[PDB]
Length: 212
Length: 213
Ligand SMILES: CC[C@]1(c2ccccc2)CCN(c2cc(C)n(CCN3CC4(CCN(c5nccn6cncc56)CC4)NC3=O)c(=O)c2)C1
Image (cartoon, rainbow over all chains, first blue to last red; front, top):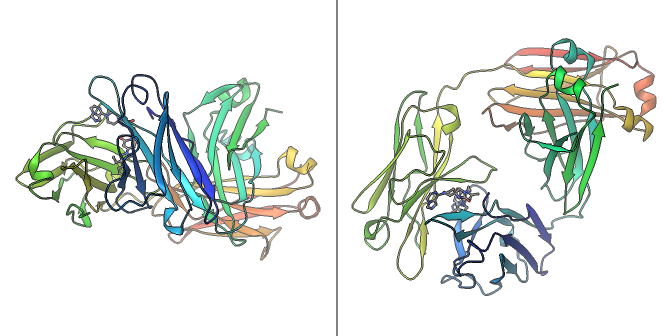
């Protein structure tokens, strides 16, 4: 996305959260045109801040917007249950364009936080004999149910062939998901290693495997 | 602040067209050409697909056409593809810096192709065994529709404890994926001749088997 938002934030009821929205001098830093939008999953989004700091009618004053340089910030004071939602920012850009952030998932904690268990599996022998070298990164027992996964070939980001499942609540009431990277046997055997990077509650865990 | 009016649902078969409407008032949809449309796959960031009533941003296929008559904007999606199955929202700026949104239309692409799961069973990784853990993962991908049941075997016998299977989720190929993981101790893993994962989808079952080495 043109603007950078942290993928997630959290707080317990009554706490405050600040989520950021970083651009460049030619968009976020070039005018006072930042807006913020709130979306509960599967419902229409809602404008909650415009022109950096302005609340539309009916938006409570615990939502506030500010800006400094090329970073805009939304602060939600006194978190309430209804504040659990995804939040997007936007700014006017260059050449009559509109730039959006990628969204921050705000969780109002409903249970204790729990860091993921991460396990990275190299290609199984059966799939290698079938000309497939899919890797799986298993991520379990975490809360909140927000996680961002990145893969690396050696040290280079890998975007192609990545899929990650939507975290789902398991029998222990914590979340699990899997990310799998669809590699050919040639790709697997010819790199020094591949890594799975799991960020949760702003903490990027990394696991690495290599051919044996 | 009033919503714009969108039908909650619309549908079409692959290759077919669908037109969905967005009715506002004279001071929003009817008052200027600032009507936008957004596509959103459940659980994902949306994508603006139309701005200024009719303009597609870069990368939006020309299968998406926007128009307006009076207070009603319309989106037509031609040549429906599986990837078009999504929620579609409209918006319009009005006066007083207000931005109005429709409630969303879920467009269903009917009759999408059935697909059997690709099932890949992974034995415990070296790292986790050194950490005194022997979790197995059965990756189940590229199936459709998105219902699956999973059963595990220790040698030939059913496993009744330690199984978790994630809720199937639709991936970028518009087919579902899930993982089942069996949380064994290294002792349980080493004390059996093999472990198997059986996936059942639309009455057909696929079984994979792994063993210590
Ligand atoms: C307003 C309600 C939002 C919403 C939230 C929840 C559900 C539904 C909608 C808030 C978050 N929204 C996003 C959020 C995101 C991430 N992306 C994708 C990222 N992109 C696409 C783009 C590309 C350039 N472009 C334009 N090209 C030419 C001329 N234009 C004039 N105006 C724009 C352009 C379109 C926008 N810029 C940008 O950063 C979106 O598209 C829209 C829309």
